Image: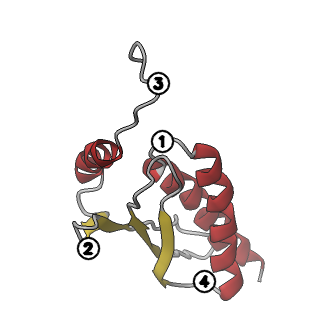
Amino acid sequence: GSSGSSGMTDYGEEQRNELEALESIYPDSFTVLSENPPSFTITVTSEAGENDETVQTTLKFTYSEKYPDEAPLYEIFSQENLEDNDVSDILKLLALQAEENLGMVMIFTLVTAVQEKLNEIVDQIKTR
């Protein structure tokens, strides 16, 4: 924690910084769609469920004018082995996550919360 960091909040810098990291952490699980505005999507795949079930949902994160100041743009470009409901649940969740994270980059965070969700859903299917 730097002495101060109170008030002036760089939005253009914050993003850039984070990205650089997402480039090393996600070498194949991160593809930059655009740059200006700087848009990119991530790839999250759940673990083999009860019957070797795996789901994947391509999320689209777009940096807005208010970020991390304000919650970023989260949308589902494509999804697999998921229904309107299952897909919705993964959304309503973020709202609470990003909402509480408001004030700082919530990229690496969202993905985390999402991953667990997919693992829970894909596993729940075992019931059927």
Write down the quadrant of residue 53 in the picture.
bottom right
Mark 2: secondary structure: loop
Residue appearing at x 43%, y 17% in the figure? 4
| Amino acid type assigned to the residue bearing label 1 in the image | Met
| Amino acid type assigned to the residue bearing label 2 in the image | Leu
Residue appearing at x 56%, y 60% in the figure? 114
Mark 2 to mark 4 CA distance (whole Å): 23 Å
Observer-side mark, 1 or 4, equals: 1
Query: Local crowd at mark 4 within 10 Å, few (<14), some, or many (≥20)?
Result: some
Q: Earlier along the polypeptide chain: callout 1 or callout 4?
A: 4
Mark 1 to mark 4 CA distance (whole Å): 30 Å
x and y, in percent, of residue 17 in the image: 27, 42
Observer-side mark, 4 or 3, equals: 3
Label 1 near label 2: C-beta < 8 Å? no
Query: Local crowd at mark 3 within 10 Å, few (<14), some, or many (≥20)?
Result: few
Which residue sits furthest front? 8
Q: Earlier along the polypeptide chain: callout 1 or callout 3?
A: 3
Q: Earlier along the polypeptide chain: callout 2 or callout 4?
A: 2
Residue labelled with disc 3: 6
Observer-side mark, 1 or 3, equals: 3
Q: Residue 82's mark?
A: 4
Observer-side mark, 2 or 1, equals: 1
Mark 1 to mark 3 CA distance (whole Å): 13 Å
Q: Residue 33's mark?
A: 2
x and y, in percent, of residue 108 in the image: 44, 49
Residue appearing at x 48%, y 41% in the figure? 104
Location of the C terminus by quadrant is bottom right
Q: In this view, does 98 lie to the left or right of 58?
A: right
| Amino acid type assigned to the residue bearing label 3 in the image | Ser
Residue labelled with disc 1: 104
